Image: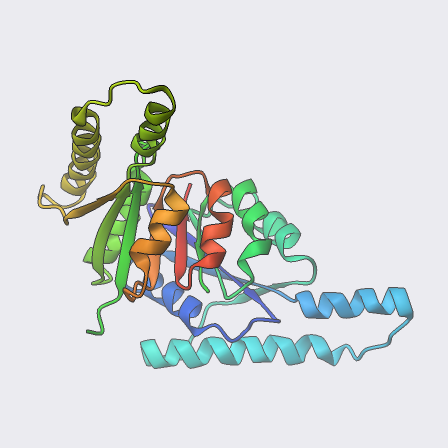
Length: 138
Length: 138
């Protein structure tokens, strides 16, 4: 299969990134790429850590709230561009971006990774540590 | 118009960069983008410098030949993808990459920059500085 394997990486903290989601849809459609979506819940992760550190409690529903904000944002763009709201399945990982992207992506052969509106300064390292093209959407 | 403006940034130093040039072509083709090409002769620049410091002769052929190799390399990939040798015009600039790209892009409305295999490690600052998406092709 010559299907360009692409991964869209989303953050629950920067779920409003139409430009990135658009790039992905265009690769999927116009370039026939095999698209997968990974959403890292970094904010939910920081909650877990504040919990351990200060004993700050938080409702398990928080996970779902983020999952839905993300999924809604996907449908909006997908429908707007594709007239359809059938989006890919979303894989959720709770932890540090770099670390989680690395784990997830390993040995899956992704030719490209599209980073959704995440602060560039913090990607510099991972992008280098990864052997695949990176599309930094600002 | 509603045609996405993309800039392909080629460099003096890093020759063999087919993958990057390829992504660029595809955007022009499948994604109907208005692609422009910019080649920063960084190696030539660093030479004019060592010239001044040491006063060693600096033949005009170096520059011309540097442009010719680049053009050849474009044609190869271009031709391999589209049966045509017809290639966009290349704009040459002689200076530090980071510096030259900022100036060139200056209010031109480019929304995406495809980096031609220049070490991603060195672009960290420039990518963050720029207000457009960056496709790092390793």
